[PDB]
Amino acid sequence: RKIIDTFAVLTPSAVSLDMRKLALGLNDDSSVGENTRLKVMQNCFEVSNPLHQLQTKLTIAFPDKSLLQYDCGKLQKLAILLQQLKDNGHRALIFTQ
Amino acid sequence: VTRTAAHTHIKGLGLDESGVAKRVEGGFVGQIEAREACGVIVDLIKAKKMSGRAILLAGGPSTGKTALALAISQELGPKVPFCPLVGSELYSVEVKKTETLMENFRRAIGLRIKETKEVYEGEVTELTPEDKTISHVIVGLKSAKGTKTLRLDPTIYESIQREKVSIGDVIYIEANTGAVKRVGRSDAYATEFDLETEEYVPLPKGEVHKKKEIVQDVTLHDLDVANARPQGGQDVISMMGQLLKPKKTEITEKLRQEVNKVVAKYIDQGVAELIPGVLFIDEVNMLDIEIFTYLNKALESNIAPVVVLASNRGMTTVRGTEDVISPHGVPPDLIDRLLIVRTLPYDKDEIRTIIERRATVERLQVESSALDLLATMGTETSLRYALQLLAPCGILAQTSNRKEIVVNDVNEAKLLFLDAKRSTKILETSANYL
Amino acid sequence: ISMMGQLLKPKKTEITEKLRQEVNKVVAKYIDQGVAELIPGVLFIDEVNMLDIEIFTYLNKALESN
Amino acid sequence: TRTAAHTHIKGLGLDESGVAKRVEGGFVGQIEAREACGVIVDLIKAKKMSGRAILLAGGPSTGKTALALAISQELGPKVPFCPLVGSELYSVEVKKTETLMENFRRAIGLRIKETKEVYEGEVTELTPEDAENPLGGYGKTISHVIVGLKSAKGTKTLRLDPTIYESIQREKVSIGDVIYIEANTGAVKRVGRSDAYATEFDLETEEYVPLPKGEVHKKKEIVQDVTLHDLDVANARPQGGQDVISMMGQLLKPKKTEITEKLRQEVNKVVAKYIDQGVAELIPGVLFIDEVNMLDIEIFTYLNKALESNIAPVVVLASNRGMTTVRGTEDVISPHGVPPDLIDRLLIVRTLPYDKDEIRTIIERRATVERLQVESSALDLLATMGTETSLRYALQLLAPCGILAQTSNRKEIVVNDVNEAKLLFLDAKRSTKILETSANYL
Amino acid sequence: KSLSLIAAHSHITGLGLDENLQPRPTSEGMVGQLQARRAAGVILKMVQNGTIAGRAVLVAGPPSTGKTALAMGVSQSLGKDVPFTAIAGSEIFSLELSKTEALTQAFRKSIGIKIKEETELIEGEVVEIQIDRSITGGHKQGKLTIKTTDMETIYELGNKMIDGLTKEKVLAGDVISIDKASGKITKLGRSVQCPEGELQKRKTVVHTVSLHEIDVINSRTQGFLALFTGDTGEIRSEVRDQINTKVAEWKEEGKAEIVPGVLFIDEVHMLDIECFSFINRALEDEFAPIVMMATNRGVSKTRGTNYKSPHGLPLDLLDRSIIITTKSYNEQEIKTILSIRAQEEEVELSSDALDLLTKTGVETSLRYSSNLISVAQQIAMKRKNNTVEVEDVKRAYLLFLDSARSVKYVQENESQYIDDQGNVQISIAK
Amino acid sequence: LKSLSLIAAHSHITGLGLDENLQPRPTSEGMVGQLQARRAAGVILKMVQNGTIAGRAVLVAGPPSTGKTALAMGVSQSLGKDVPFTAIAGSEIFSLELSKTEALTQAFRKSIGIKIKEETELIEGEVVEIQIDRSITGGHKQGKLTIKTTDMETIYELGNKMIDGLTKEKVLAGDVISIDKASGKITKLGRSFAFVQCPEGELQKRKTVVHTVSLHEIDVINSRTQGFLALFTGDTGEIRSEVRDQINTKVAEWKEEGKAEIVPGVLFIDEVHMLDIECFSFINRALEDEFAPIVMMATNRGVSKTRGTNYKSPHGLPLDLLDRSIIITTKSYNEQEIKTILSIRAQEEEVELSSDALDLLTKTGVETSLRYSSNLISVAQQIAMKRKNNTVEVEDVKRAYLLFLDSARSVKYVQENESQYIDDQGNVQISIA
Ligand SMILES: Nc1ncnc2c1ncn2[C@@H]1O[C@H](COP(=O)(O)OP(=O)(O)O)[C@@H](O)[C@H]1O
Ligand SMILES: Nc1ncnc2c1ncn2[C@@H]1O[C@H](COP(=O)(O)OP(=O)(O)O)[C@@H](O)[C@H]1O
Ligand SMILES: Nc1ncnc2c1ncn2[C@@H]1O[C@H](COP(=O)(O)OP(=O)(O)O)[C@@H](O)[C@H]1O
Ligand SMILES: Nc1ncnc2c1ncn2[C@@H]1O[C@H](COP(=O)(O)OP(=O)(O)O)[C@@H](O)[C@H]1O
Ligand SMILES: [Mg+2]
Ligand SMILES: [Mg+2]
Ligand SMILES: [Mg+2]
Ligand SMILES: [Mg+2]
Ligand SMILES: [Mg+2]
C-alpha cells in the first residue's frame, strides 16, 4: 500500500463520462433485461476489490502532505539548515511580516 | 549535478531575424545552409497553412542530422507538440504497423481546451440512505464558512461507502467526473481517542462550493482514446469495464471522423485552438515498403501534420522489396512528395571547435596541445571517438590529481581504448574469431 | 459472469470431436423418432488451387467421413 | 504389469567404491560409460556444484537414454528429475527462453519438515474455574477452562487459559464430539461427531468419526516437498473465489505469463530465510533434454548465460547426430549439433555399439521382463537378425512371435515362428529396398 | 465546418462536367485530362443510375499524373448521402483480422440503406409543471403546461411520464421536445429558440445505415460499440446470409432502399494474391459496390508469386476490370495547375516567377514545384514584400534539393554514405 | 543476507580489485591477470560512481575463454549495493507477448532507480497489562493498555482500529511490541520474560525510512489500475509512450525539488553478436536520451553476418553502433596464469590439490581449453573420495581424463566412426554387420 500511495501519480487526462455504463451494456435503455441490470448493479455494489487504492489514486491526483516545502524555494534550504542547527545544539528565531 | 548525453549543448538553431545563420551560435559550428533551410521549415510550421508536407535530411554519419532535428524541436517551443519516433518502433505485435503509423499522426496534433470544474469540500455531518435500485444519499458537508447539504448519485455513494467515510470526516468530492477523496478525520475529534492510526486534518477553509478554469492541453489522440475505450473510475463497474478489454484495438475511420467533428464544434465556440506538430522518424531506412506505400496516401490527407524523416544511406534496396533499388532506402514514388535537406561533413577546424564547446559544456579544462591531439584523432578516426575519449581523460586526470588534460593522459586513453579501425585490424589477424 | 460472457466478442474455437459425436447421437435419435429429418447439402469451393497441401491432405480424411 | 522398451533397467548397477560390474541392473557392457555416469551420481549427491552440464554422445540404439533413466533411478524418487525434449521448448503461449528458464527451475526441489504436538479425543465435559479478578468487580471471573479428552486406551484432563473460550465458541463444540487441539498454536478444530452417537437419530446429515486411536496426546512430524517453480506459480497466480480479480479469472482464460526476475529473487529471499533457520532443505535436481540437436541457436545461446547462474542445476544432454549445421545458421558446422562455445562448457561421454555376444544377452534378458521364454536355437537367429537388420528389430519381434506361438498353442518360440514373424513385419532396410523396385510411388 | 488546413486535393471539387459529359478545359479545379474526365463521368452517371452493380474499373497512368485526383473528383461530385470508401492496399492487412474478412468488410461498408420511421412529437415551452406525491386516490397526479405560439394546451401526465420528468431535473421556462412513442425527452434550448407552432406534429425520420453497420449489431450483444472500436473480429457468414434476405424482404415491403456506393482502392499493386483471388468472387455477387482501382506501377511481380504479371495484377482480375489510362501533362497545363494551387494557398506569383516554376515543373516534376510554391512564400515573407520574386524561387531552389540532383550528388559522395554491403568511411584522411 | 548460493563459475570473483591509483594488482579479489582490461573497466567503475555523465556505450571484445563476462561480473560486484545492475542475454529480448523494441526500452527503464526518503514515528516499549471493553451483540468496544519502558511508564487508550490490530496478533504483558502511529502495523521483536531486555531510551522515537523504486516499476504502475499486478505476474505490453513522456517530466520535477534523487545504474548485455537489426537501430537513437544507463556489452564472435541482413559486418555489429561505442579488447592467458586460475578455483571449491596434479592439470589445461580444466577439478575430488583420503593425485586426474572426453578428442572419434553417427544428409548405419 505504501509504494502504491507514493509512486502513483499520472491521471488519464482525457475521459468520456457515461462510457462505463454503456460499455457493460447496463444503462437506462438497452437490450438487456430490466431486472437483470438491477441485480448486476447490486452484485457490483456488494462485491469488493483490493484494487480500490490504485483506482482512487489513479483517478484523482493527490497533493498528499508533501508539497508544502517542495513548492517553496525558501523552504528547500530551510529544513536543511534547521537540521544543521539541530545537530549542532543551537536555537533559532524566525521573524516574519 | 547536470547529466549530459550527446546533447544539451544545443539550445536551438541560432538564426537571426533576417534568416542568416551565424558561424557559431548555440553549440552549432558550420552547417549554415541546413540551419537556414531548417529555420524556413520552422516558420512554415508557425504559419500553420501547410499540411501533409514531408522534409527529409540525408547526410553521412556524424554529420549532425539528428542533432539538427532536435534544434527545430527546441525552436518550436514546449507549446508545440513534438513526437520523436524511430522506424523500428512501427513494428508491433499487438496491433498492425499501419494503425501504429496512423496513430502518431493524431498524436502529433495538439489541441488545448479550457473548462471549469466545480469542487465541494467540507466535514460530513449526516449520512442517510434513501432506501432493486441503489438509492441516493443526502450528504451534510460542513464548510468552515458555511453549511450546505447536497444529494448525490448512487454511484458516488458506492465510492463513498468504499472509502469507509464516517460522520465527522473531511472528504473531497469532484463534481464533473464524480471523483471522491477523503483528506482525513476532522481536527475537532482528535481528542476522542488517545491512540489512533488515523491522521487529523484541519477543516477546509472557504466556501463549500468552489470553481476555477484550467487551460489544460490534451493531445488529440489522448482525446480519441477516451471515446474509444473506457477509463479508470472509483466504481467497480468501471474497473470491470476497463478490465474486460485491456488490449489495445485498432480505431475505425468513422470514430476518428466523428471526434474530428466534435473538435470542430469545440473550435466554433472559441473554447479550443487546434495547432499542428512535427513527427520525427529516425532511421527511415528500416521501414518496410508497406509503411512507405501507406505514407503515400496518408500524407495526402488534410489532417496529416508535417513529418520529418532522417536516413543515412547510398543507393540501396528498400526493405521488403526484391529488385527495387532507390536512393536513401526510400521508394521513388514517396521521394517525390519529399523535399531534401543536404548535410555536409566538417573540416578539421570545425571538429576542433566541436570538441572545444563540448568540453566547455561538459565542464572540463583541456590544454591546447592535448586539444590538438584530439583534433588529429578526430581526423584520423572519427568525430564521435574524439568526443567519446573526453571523459576517460578527465578520469585519469582525477587519478593523477591534475585539473587539466595532458598529452600523456590522452595518449594513455588511446592505449586503453580502441576505435573500430584498430579492432577490425585485430579481427583480420587473430587465432579464433577474437 | 454470463453477462460479461455475452459482452465479449464471439471468438471462433476448435470444436472437439466428442461434442460433434453427441450432437450426431441426439440427432440420430430424433431421426429415429421421426420428429426430425436430416437432408444433405452441397459445398462449393472456388479457386481450389489456392489451398495449401495441408488442407488438401485433410480433405482426404474429411471426404471419408459419413 | 506394463513394459514399454524399458523397466529391465534397475539403477546404474555399480558396486561399492569400485569398477562397475559386468552385468547388473539389466545393463550389459559399456562399463566405462555407466562408471563415468556413476561419478556424476556422486557429484549430484554432493549438492554443491551448480550449472554443471554433461553430454553423452553416440550412435543410435547405443543405450544413450537408458543411462539417463539409470542415473534417474540412482538418485532416488525424492530427488526431482524432469524428462524434457528439445522440441518442447517451442510454445505459442510464451517465448522459448521463458519456457527454458521455467524448466531450469523445475529441477530443484525444496523439502519442509514440521513437528507439532496435538491433543485429540472425545469431550467428557467442560467446566469453568472461577477465581478473583485482579481488580475488584461484581461480575464473574474465570481463571481457567477445564477440558477432558477421551481416546482409545487412555483418558486425560486439561487446563487452558480463559482465552480458549473464543476459539471453542468459534468451533461450536460442546460435549461428546471429537475435537482437534494443537499445543502451542492453540485454538481448536472440529473433525466430526463421535461414532457412538449415530444410533440416537434414525436420520442425520452429520457423519460420525470414531474416537482417535492411541494416546490423547501425540507428537508427529510431516515432511512436505515442493519445487521452486511450483512455489513461484502460486505466488504469481491470484487465489480467491469471489474476488473481482478472481472474478476476471472466470469467463476469461489463464495463459502462461513470463515471470519477472524480481519475483523469482523475492521467492529466493524467503526460501533462504527458511533455509537459514533449519526448517527448509534445498536439494538440487537434474534436468534432462533428449535430442538436443532440435534446439535453435537462440536457446543454445541462452544456455551459455543460464548455466553460469548460481542456482542452476545439473543438466544432462543427449545428441546422437554427428557433424551437422546448427539450427538457425546454415554455414556453421559443429559436432553433435551443439555450438563450440556451448561444447566448451560441458564434458563429453562417449558411447560404443554393443557386441554380438552382448546383443544375444540383451535379448535373453529382455525375455525375462517380457515373461516369454525362448529356446537356444531360435535365440541364435534373433542374434544374427539383431546384428544384421538392427538391434531394436529383434526386440520388436519378441511379442509377435509370442502371439503367433499362442495361435499355434505352443508356449515357447520356435524357428518357424520367428521366420513367420519375419515375413509379416519388415525392417527399414527391406522396405527401403522395396521402394526402389516399385514405380507405383510406393 | 470540419476544420481542415490544406490538402493536396483541397482545390479540385467535384471534377467537372457538362450536360453533354464533354469536359471543360478548366472546370471546378480540374484542368487537363480530357478523356479521363469523360470516362470517369460515365462511371459517375453509372453510379447515380444504380442499375448495375459489382463492376470493376481500373485507372492506370504515370506517377503524379491525373490519377488520385480523378477518384477525388468522382467522390466529391457524387456528393453527400451516397457512400464512398477509400482504403490503401496496406490497410487491409491486419494482425487481428484476416485479409479476406477485412476485404469483405469494405464491400459491406460501401453499400448503405435508408430506413424511414414516423413519429408523433410534442414540443414547446414549459411554463408550469406540477407533480404530486402518491396518494390513495391515484398513483400520481400531475399537470404540465406546454406553451407554443399558435396553441397552448395542458396535458395530464401518464405515470411513467412523471418518472421521466422527475428522472431528469427539468426547470420551467426551457424548450423541450417530448417523444410519445420513444418515451424520452429532448431539450432543444431555453426560453435561444422560439415556439414555431402546433404542439403535436407527425414527422418521418430517415436513417442511412450501411450493410456493415446492420451486420455488426446482430452478431454482438452491443455491436454499435464494435463499429467504433474495430474489435469486430470476423463476423460469421451465416449472420450476413440472414442480413441479405431480411434486406430483400425490407425492399419488397418498401420500408427500406439501398444506395449503390463506390469503393476506391489506392495502391492496389501491393495487395496480396489471395485478396485478388477473393475479389473475383466478391464482384459477381448480388450486393457489391462499384470498384475503382489505381496502380502506378506496371510490368512487375505480383506479391505472393515468383512470376511477373503485366501491370502488377493477375489477368483473372484484369478480365473483370475496365482499364482507363491517363497521360502525362503538357507544359501549358502545368502552369495553369500551379496557378490553381497559387489561388488555393493564397500565394501571389509573378509571371516571371511562373515561367521559371513552369520550366522547373517540366524538367523535374509537378509535385516538386507545387511543394516549392508553398516554401517560397516564407522567404518572401522575410523580405516583407507581399508578392513572390524570382530571387526567392532561386533561393528556394538551391536550399531544397531535387531528387535527380540528390542522386547525382550521392553517386559522387557514395564513399561517405552507407552502402548495401555496410561499408562507410567516417575518417577524412588516409 | 545470503541469497540461495551454490558453487558457480563466477563465484570466486568479488570486486574488481583495483588500486587507488587504478592500476591492477597481479592477484587480487579473485581476479588474476588481464591488466589493461581490469583498469579500463575500473575507469568505467569510477565513471558510474561519478554519475555526472549519461548515454555512453562501451564494448568488451575477445576470444572464448577470456573473462570479459567475468570482468563485467567483477564490475557488478565492485559496483556494490544500492546501484541497480541489469544483465540480459541477447536472445532474451525476443518475445511473443511484447515487441522487441518495447522490451528493449523496458531493459533501459530497469537500470536507473530512484530513492525517496521519509520520516515515520515509532513507539517501542513493554506492556504492563491489557484492558478491553466489549459487549455481546453490543457493538462499540473500548480498549486500554499500559506501555512501560525504563525511563517512561505511561498509559494509552485504544482506538477503534487499534482494537482489531491488537486482536489480530496476540499481545500480552510479557510480549514487547513496536507500533508505528501512521502505519498502524504491529511489530513483535520477540518474547521478553516468560529473551530481549527492555528497550533503552525514550518510548516514542522518530526514524527515517527510505524507499527505492526503479523507473520501470513507476512506468508499469501508472499504466492501468491492475497494472500493479503486471509487476509480479510479469504480464504487460505496449506501454503508452505518453506515459513515459509524462513520467520523465514528473521525475525531472522531483529532481529539481530535491524530493527524490536518482541513482544511475549499469546495463549489461551478454551475447550481443546475435540481435535483430531493428534493435541496433533503436539503440543508436535510444542512447541519446537524458536518462540513458551506461551500456556495456560482450561479443566473442569474429567477423560474421548480422541477423536480419545478408551482408557480413565486422565484429558482428553494424558500424553505426561501433561508432559511439568504445571497444575494450581482451587477450589470451599465459600458461602460468591458467595454473593460478585453477589454484584459486581449488580454493573457492575448497579442494586440496597435489603439486604434480596441479602441473599436469595445468599442462592438459593449456593444451585444451581452460574451462575444461576447471571442469575436471570438481570431479577429481569425487573420484578421490572413494580412495577415502582427501587429496588430488595424478592417477585420479588421469582416470578423470579418460572418463570425460575433450571436444578436440571427440572430433576425431566422430570422424572415424561417421558411418555410425547420423550424417547431415540423414544416413546412419545402426548395424554392426
Ligand atoms: N554543427 C554541429 N555543432 C555541434 N555539434 C554537432 C554538430 N553536428 C553534429 N554534432 C554532434 O555530433 C553528435 C552526433 O551527431 P548525430 O546527429 O548523431 O549524427 P547522425 O545524424 O549521423 O546520427 C551529436 O551529439 C552532436 O552534438
Ligand atoms: N546395457 C544394456 N542392456 C540391455 N539393453 C540395453 C542396454 N543399453 C541399451 N539397451 C536397449 O536400448 C534401448 C534404448 O536405446 P536408446 O538409448 O533410446 O537409443 P538412442 O541411443 O538412439 O537414444 C532400450 O530399449 C534397451 O533395451
Ligand atoms: N487534372 C488535374 N488538375 C489539377 N491538379 C492535378 C491534376 N492531376 C494531378 N494534379 C495534382 O497532382 C497532385 C497529386 O497527384 P496524384 O493524382 O495523386 O498522382 P498519383 O495519383 O499518380 O499519385 C495533386 O496535388 C494535384 O494538385
Ligand atoms: N581474470 C580472471 N580471474 C578469474 N577467473 C577468470 C578470469 N578470466 C577468466 N576466468 C574464468 O573463465 C571462466 C569463464 O570464462 P568466460 O569469460 O565466461 O568465457 P566467455 O568469454 O566465452 O564468456 C570463469 O569460470 C572464470 O573463472
Ligand atoms: Mg541519427
Ligand atoms: Mg533417446
Ligand atoms: Mg495514387
Ligand atoms: Mg470466376
Ligand atoms: Mg560469454
Image (cartoon, coloured by chain):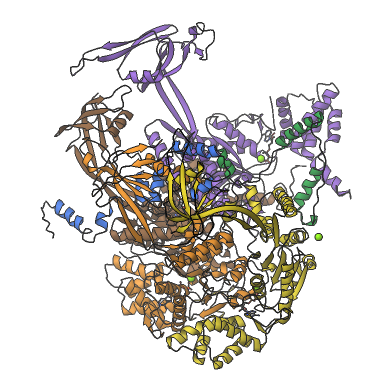
Chain colours: A blue, B orange, C green, D purple, E yellow, F brown
In the image, is A83 to the left or to the right of E292? left
**At x 35% / y 76%, what residue is drawn?**
B357
In the image, is F171 to the left or to the right of F306? left
Determine if residue F293 is in view: no
Determine if residue E14 is in view: yes
The picture places residue E56, in percent across and down from the top left corner, at: 75, 67
Q: Residue E408's image quarter?
A: bottom right
Judging depth in this view, the residue of E170 and F189 nearest the camera is E170
The residue at the far bottom in this view is E352
In the image, is F133 to the left or to the right of D398? left
Image quarter (top left, top right, bottom left or bottom right) of the C terminus of chain F = top right
The picture places residue F218, in percent across and down from the top left corner, at: 40, 52
Q: Is residue D154 above or below residue B331?
A: above
In the image, is D440 to the left or to the right of F239? right
Judging depth in this view, the residue of D387 and B209 nearest the camera is B209
The picture places residue D176, in percent across and down from the top left corner, at: 43, 9
Count of labels in the image? 0
The quarter of the image that holds ligand 8 is bottom right
Judging depth in this view, the residue of B387 and C48 nearest the camera is C48
Q: Is residue D135 above or below residue E254?
A: above
Judging depth in this view, the residue of E77 and F398 nearest the camera is E77
**At x 25% / y 39%, what residue is drawn?**
F181
Image quarter (top left, top right, bottom left or bottom right) of the N terminus of chain F = top left
Q: Is residue E418 above or below residue D193?
A: below
**At x 26% / y 57%, what residue is drawn?**
A70
The picture places residue E394, in percent across and down from the top left corner, at: 52, 89
